[PDB]
Image: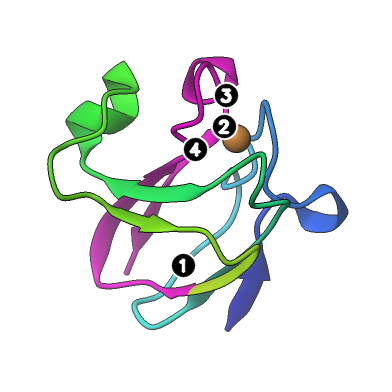
Amino acid sequence: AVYVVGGSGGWTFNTESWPKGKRFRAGDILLFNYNPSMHNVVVVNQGGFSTCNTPAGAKVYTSGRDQIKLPKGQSYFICNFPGHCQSGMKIAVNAL
Ligand SMILES: [Cu+2]
């Protein structure tokens, strides 16, 4: 199944809450919509998610319409533009 992160508002600020009440499965797809001149999608670990620090080698997406397939387990995504992560532009999901 495909989920549009943030619904009609897309990938934006103060969105950490979006995952709340959703049940993800391995193989599900997260679709991220945004203006790439102003935002990105970065795949980090739990640590990076918590401190808003991008680990070395983290994958960065910048298409504006990214389709990310979820592996089994935990996945963490942040926007690493200055101050975005700190403003709630991050999500944590668990895929069963
Ligand atoms: Cu951003």
Q: Name the residue under label 3.
A: 88
Looking at the image, residue 3 sits to the left or right of residue 40; the answer is: right
Q: Is residue 87 magenta?
A: yes
Q: Quadrant of the N terminus?
A: bottom right
Disc 3 to disc 2, how far (Cα)?
4 Å
Q: Which of marks 4 and 2 is nearer the N terminus?
A: 4
Tag 3 secondary structure: loop
* Tag in front: 1 or 2: 2
Determine whether 12 is above or below 29 in the image.
above
Tag 2 secondary structure: loop
**Whole-percent x and y of residue 76?**
34, 46
Q: Give the range drawn in magenta.
A: 68-96
Q: Does the residue labelled 2 lie within 8 Å of ligand 1?
A: yes
Q: Name the residue under label 1.
A: 24
Q: Are marks 4 and 1 in contact (CB under 8 Å)?
A: no
Q: Do the residues labelled 1 and 2 touch (CB within 8 Å)?
A: no
Q: Are marks 4 and 2 in contact (CB under 8 Å)?
A: yes
Q: Name the residue under label 4.
A: 79
Disc 4 to disc 1, how far (Cα)?
21 Å
Q: Residue furthest left?
A: 56
Q: Do the residues labelled 3 and 2 touch (CB within 8 Å)?
A: yes
Which quadrant does ligand 1 occupy? top right
Looking at the image, residue 10 sits to the left or right of residue 91; the answer is: right
Disc 4 to disc 2, how far (Cα)?
6 Å
Looking at the rendered structure, the kind of residue marked 3 is: Gly
Tag 4 secondary structure: loop
Looking at the rendered structure, the kind of residue marked 1 is: Phe
Looking at the image, residue 20 sits to the left or right of residue 91; the answer is: right
Q: Does the residue labelled 4 lie within 8 Å of ligand 1?
A: yes
- On residue 89, the disc is 2
Q: Does the magenta stretch include residue 21?
A: no
